[PDB]
Amino acid sequence: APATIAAGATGELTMYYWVPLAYSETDLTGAVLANVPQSKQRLKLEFAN
Amino acid sequence: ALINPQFPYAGPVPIPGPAPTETMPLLNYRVEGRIAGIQQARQFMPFLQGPHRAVAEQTYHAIGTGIQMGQTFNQPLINTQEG
Image (tube, rainbow over the protein chains, first blue to last red):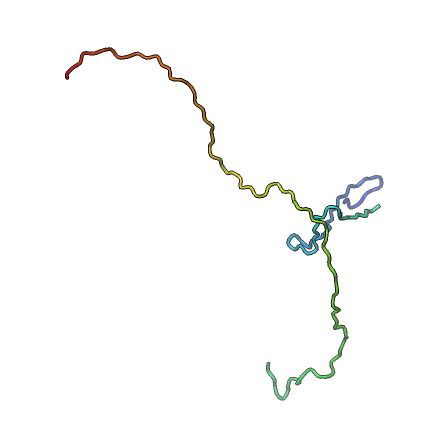
């Protein structure tokens, strides 16, 4: 993200988030078994405005 | 441990100690846990169970056909030697 955005300018930003279920790549504590067809998961994202 | 007389090590931590809390209790956990989503019998993979050929042998089919035909030229007659 640009440190500053001057009057009249447009800045571009990139951001990444990892939303964990499992604790880590080797510790599956918290993971979710999703093999039940009719029954969906929901990941709600509320963005800045 | 060394004890040295006359300065002896108190014979205990005595009764002047400050009990700081009664927070000693771990409340037992009571819970009901249900992991029940419909399971479907199948998973898709690229390949499971195959033991792929690293080299094949050479393989073939077979045919023959024809008849017995011929054009011939013979050696001339010769004088017989002996017998």
